[PDB]
Image 1 (spheres, rainbow, N blue to C red):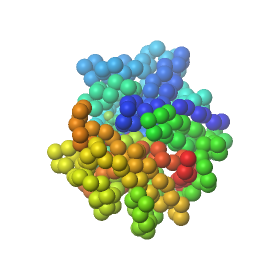
Image 2 (cartoon, protein in one colour):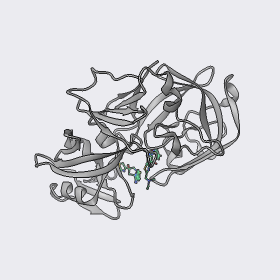
Image 3 (cartoon, rainbow, N blue to C red):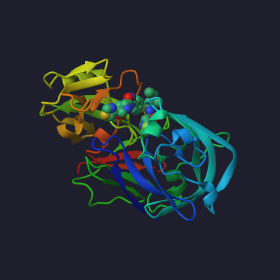
Image 4 (tube, rainbow, N blue to C red):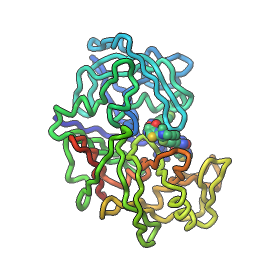
Length: 330
Ligand SMILES: C#CCN(C)Cc1nc([C@]2(O)CN[C@@H](c3nc(-c4ccc(F)cc4)no3)C2)cs1
């Protein structure tokens, strides 16, 4: 089997991407944030505290003939930005782009933190990291991809995120028309439960390439590119007036600037992030200070190849027995 679904930016900044997902019978379509950095599929639901729901579409398990309470199971998760959610668990039929998993754990939110309430366009998350990170207790649950894997034509999914434009998540096949050149595959460590890999270095603009190992994760659920302070400083040093602002919480730059590109290494291959992808616009409406799309990972504890990096590439998440990540230009 295979599946193919379009993913769409939630706003003009590409802050996140949402993908329609069918849950239950008859189908209830919710727009979920596919997150290769976590492993819970959770949804706003008829159980979510009413004061914490503001415009989201909710899953109502009592209206699904295929829903079953996963008796006694609870879940509770926090994300890198400090957001969080928790609740109980149903199993139900879940379909993404024509690919169906029966008996998928659908984690129903009883509580969500303010950032989720405020994002009226995000009806929940669909985790695509390794199932070892799933938070369901006392019986840990598998991700949608893990459940689908044995039925897929190939044990892979691909992320083809757009820049201020829709893109595609495919399951079970590699669309050879979606990229240019070759896909360079690189080894993955699952030791932390992430799609963790080692980039071979970087370049700023038209500069020479610096060969240096950068361990990090491929995370579709993170907006920005978080890299070591040394790398980030070398990038922003090329932008007149750019500075790290403690009040803003990261690097800002004059909105009058044209940003240089940023290249990252994948083995002997290179992915070039255009400068425009690094511009997240005014820090507040009307401001002439713009927020940078490359930020320091210092204090996160991990480098994160988030959407800023991933949307410059066609990315293969190969979940074979020895997992790998593939990157191609596009
Ligand atoms: C700090 C620290 C140490 N480590 C836990 C950092 C990491 N953190 C992650 C993720 O939690 C998993 N992916 C990303 C994600 N964030 C969201 C999200 C958050 C709030 C919203 F309102 C909407 C979406 N969705 O996915 C971050 C991986 S490593």
